[PDB]
Image: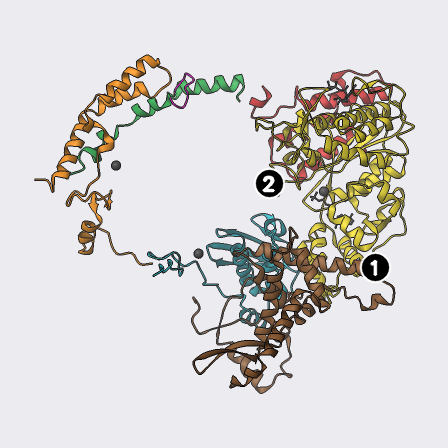
Chain colours: A brown, B red, C cyan, D yellow, E green, F orange
Amino acid sequence: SRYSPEFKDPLIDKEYYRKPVEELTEEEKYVRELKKTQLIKAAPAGKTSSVFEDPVISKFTNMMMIGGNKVLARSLMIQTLEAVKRKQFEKYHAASAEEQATIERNPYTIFHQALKNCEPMIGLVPILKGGRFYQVPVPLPDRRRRFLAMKWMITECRDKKHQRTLMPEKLSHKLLEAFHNQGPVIKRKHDLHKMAEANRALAHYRWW
Amino acid sequence: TEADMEEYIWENSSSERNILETLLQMKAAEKNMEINKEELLGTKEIEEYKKSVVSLKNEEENENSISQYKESVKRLLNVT
Amino acid sequence: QGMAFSKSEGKRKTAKAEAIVYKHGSGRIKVNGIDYQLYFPITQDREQLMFPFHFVDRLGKHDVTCTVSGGGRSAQAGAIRLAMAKALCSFVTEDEVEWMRQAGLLTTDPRVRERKKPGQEGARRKFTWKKR
Amino acid sequence: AISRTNENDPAKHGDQHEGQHYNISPQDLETVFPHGLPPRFVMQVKTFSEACLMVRKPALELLHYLKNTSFAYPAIRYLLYGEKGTGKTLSLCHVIHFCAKQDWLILHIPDAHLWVKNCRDLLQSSYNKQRFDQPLEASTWLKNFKTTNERFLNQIKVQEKYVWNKRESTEKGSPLGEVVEQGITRVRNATDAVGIVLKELKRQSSLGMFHLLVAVDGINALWGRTTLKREDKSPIAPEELALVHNLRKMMKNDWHGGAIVSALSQTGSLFKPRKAYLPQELLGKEGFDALDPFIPILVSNYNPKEFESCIQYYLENNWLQHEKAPTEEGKKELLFLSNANPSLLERHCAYL
Amino acid sequence: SLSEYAFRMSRLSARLFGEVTRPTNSKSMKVVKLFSELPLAKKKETYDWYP
Amino acid sequence: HYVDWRMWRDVKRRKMAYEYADERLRINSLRKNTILPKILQDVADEEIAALPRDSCPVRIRNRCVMTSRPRGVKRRWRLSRIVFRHLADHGQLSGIQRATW
Ligand SMILES: Nc1nc2c(ncn2[C@@H]2O[C@H](COP(=O)(O)OP(=O)(O)NP(=O)(O)O)[C@@H](O)[C@H]2O)c(=O)[nH]1
Ligand SMILES: Nc1ncnc2c1ncn2[C@@H]1O[C@H](COP(=O)(O)OP(=O)(O)OP(=O)(O)O)[C@@H](O)[C@H]1O
Ligand SMILES: [Mg+2]
Ligand SMILES: [Mg+2]
Ligand SMILES: [Mg+2]
């Protein structure tokens, strides 16, 4: 890194700075007076202080980027969000007054919930015991759970099973399926739970 | 030829030929027999139109030159 | 004409920018004499021009005229962001300047391209360790 | 309904309606606009279940000129120009809707750039061996032309004998609809059927039969370059295309009884830089000479009033789903990122 | 692809600046290049390469 | 007293190429055009092909002037990479230094 260890990461949050002084504790007062003497890295060109910023969608976009082509990756993302919203507006106008109350039309709410429905609770990690590796079911950290949900969704959309279907139409279709606890990405989560439940006998190999 | 000229000249150009042909059709529509070229191309409106076309041809095109050209065409075509 | 303004500079990779921020304006930004949305057709680049003014709650309050040369489209948007942020510090309170500093808006990004070394494919990429 | 207006008659729109959206009935969308609406605006009509068009000064200015048209003078050429996505096409459509409801005959070319690029079947013409026909492009337009002017294609009757083959021919006095059906049924005669339509309308409008509106979006394609190639992979010129050759005749002000309203467009053009939009820069020297004298009409970005009414029209349809979009801080970001450009704003709001 | 005026103007500028006046194809223009420079074998770097 | 027999052969090639350069140039000009008759150009082809082999400049090789190494030579100094480095690494080449950046 071209930053020395003395550089601290920037905090990009308008609310954090407009907070009155009276509400601050003696510990939060120390951190604010400390940062006035520290070196701060330049804010990356990715995140800003915008009110439409979504760190989860930004991360999903980078995981779709091929060869640093962010423009194309970002283009596929907004086309998916538009495709999801148009499908929900079409399902909304074609529904009855009672069914309309249960139809979600916010693509950001659908995207977050669809990924949350695909996150696995437990995984298989190799543990060495007696000179052999055993696939031991273990709890996954929050980072790993969220990462696996995104990776499974992107991998499913790149599968060759889809013939000539463009990414925004494929992804929008998979998100709405996962949003309703259906589709192949939900099935992949169930398989990891079934394969972790089969190795239930090896769970005691864990030591944390 | 005209393609060899590096400075646009309004005389004997398509602009002069087109505007003159238009004013003759307008005079005929009004059933007026004052079809003299020297009279039609001698008014002040033609001088403003000539000045506007030459500016668009020889100088850099911009919004102010297109607006000046617009006001000169509206007066010749009686578009108020 | 008696209109107060400030001037500053910024660098990002090989791009160099120089911005003139007027104390009063309507939010107009000219990049090399072009409207900013015509010069930066990519939305991410325009989001970088919005970051400084939005972070201090001053969208639509200043006019900016900047000139940028070198680098690519994203590096130029980054150099303009730093140049406008520095010049904008003249029209905000001292406490607001410290917030911009802690938000990473006043730091020159030192990340530049690394040279290729001889005997390897890239700056870090090595040639394939031949199968033994 | 702060962004809507109850006045749905384009003949009654005035300066008091600026910035307000008026509704186009589903009947007029099927008849008047089988083509020409921007593709993304067509998506909005399907999504909002309605077609609403904002009343703006460019269209109001042009509607003022058309209501004072002197049908005895030669047709006047009006040219809409402006930066990309400012609303040139939809300003033309608002004017097409006015003349359509005034019982004018509408000759609408929705996108002339499609006639100079990406042509798979570019056949040689039989009427003139030095020109090329375009059966697919010509037959497509004939179908839409029939839908818009269906009620006039029987009253209008040809005034000459047209020979399609050794066996088929359109005798004098036959309805103009027979010429349109010959081109639709036989695509090999589509290009010549289009040429006969433009020939009859221009002829019979000068006789007082009807009022004619010539609406060409992308007019800068007629005097530019083409990407079509001959069998010897040599470039073809626009004048060598039968469709372009005949459409150039309609742009001449050698007829009366109507008007000529066109709109420039860099989008879809050939060999033009991204930021070109002024008349001479898009028309070129040959194009500016073919239209001069004309009346250019500028189309710019939304003004503060128009921008606010556009946001209210989206919020009124629940299109902006992000919880921060209705807030004041959310509108300032939408205004900055689009710089009030109608097209940039519609695209940003499409995924919010 | 030049007008008769441009063609005659280019031939006039060629005579004044001492260029080739007759129409000459690319192959025959190698004769001009051959005699406009010294052959490689005649350059001092070539025949005095070694001390 | 040249480094080896291979350098001596290149010395003779450079000498003979210099002596026939004007003649070869004049004959080649007759061949490199579409203006003269083919009958005359075919005779010029035979004439230049009858000149001595060692008059042809493509047979000259840029060898190291101190060791006669036929490859790895830097044209600007006419030295092989090995000899060049020996002089450079002892600070005997004006203005040349190791590059670090
Ligand atoms: N098949 C067919 N097409 C015709 C006939 N008459 C006219 N057309 C079509 O209508 C177009 C316009 O008609 P017209 O002005 O007479 O054509 P033109 O003789 O080519 N005129 P110009 O000299 O200006 O090129 C023609 O180019 C042709 O495509 C006809 O009898 N048969
Ligand atoms: N009068 C209007 N009413 C409603 N929306 C409009 C209007 N004018 C422009 N828009 C919005 O802006 C978009 C672009 O409009 P339009 O395609 O007419 O612009 P243009 O300047 O002709 O574009 P181009 O430069 O690509 O030809 C429309 O799809 C719509 O979302
Ligand atoms: Mg690499
Ligand atoms: Mg358009
Ligand atoms: Mg060699």
Q: Position of residue F63 (x, y in %)?
A: 19, 41
Q: Is residue D141 visible?
A: yes
Label 2 CA crowd tier, 10 Å (few <14, some 14–19, many 20+): few
In this view of the protein, which residue sits in the foreground, E25 or D83? E25
Q: Secondary structure at mark 1?
A: helix
Q: Is residue D161 left or right of residue F99?
A: right
- Label 2 element class: loop
Establish if D296 lies above or below C70: above
Q: For residue D88, what is the image quadrant?
A: top right
Q: Which residues are magenta?
A: E20-27
Label 2 with label 1: CB-CB less than 8 Å:
no
Viewer-side residue, F72 vs C61: F72
Q: Locate residue E49, reporting x and y percent.
A: 18, 37
Q: Which disc is residue D273 wearing? A: 2
Q: Name the chain under label 2.
A: D
Question: Do the residues at pointers 2 and 1 share their chain?
Answer: no
Depth check: give the residue in front, C113 or D152.
D152
The answer to which image quadrant residue D238 occupies is top right
Which x, y percent locates residue B40? Answer: 76, 20
Q: Residue at x 33, y 56 (%)?
A: C118
Q: Which mark is residue A93?
A: 1
Please check the rendered image and state whether residue A200 is part of the magenta-colored stretch, yes or no: no
